[PDB]
Image (cartoon, rainbow, N blue to C red):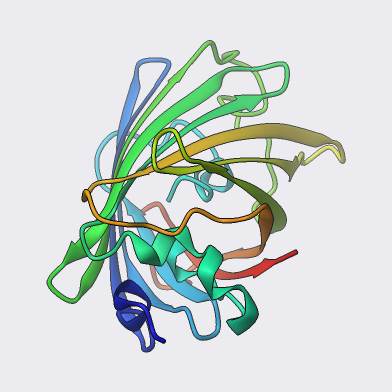
Length: 226
């Protein structure tokens, strides 16, 4: 049978993202608008910086800026924690260790507001080197992929995940970002605790030729597997 929360994602769902960030005392805000279609695991979004000068590369913010839009194959639907927590939603927490540099710590609440999926985020970054790859803006703006490895966290009625992102440096090298993640439902009802599996993710960053504010256009595909 079709799950309650699963039925909320059969079609195109509008998305709003709101992030407040503080990286080594540099404050910034990001507003995102777009849509997701979990039938195809497809997200299309436009992000705009609204306050302080964006102190970090846009690519380092992709993973923080809604895994309920993952396409879960039919044979895997009973391992989809994310949709099962809806519409009340879940809290997502991460620490993102940038190798030989600082870390982000994030807390996000993901839920429906009416028919819109909303991601509200607070982001704190510390210990970043002021001429490093992040504060020095030395990362390429193009494309990366990821495998989010998900395990059940039945103590907290949620999940844990960890994964690595390799961000291309302009010089040719790679800036590693080690992600550690926990998700806990906001409601008190039953959620699907999954067997071990992963999310295969692909992110394509682009620019709106007409847009003069600091911004990021994102096309993303997310597919459960394993």
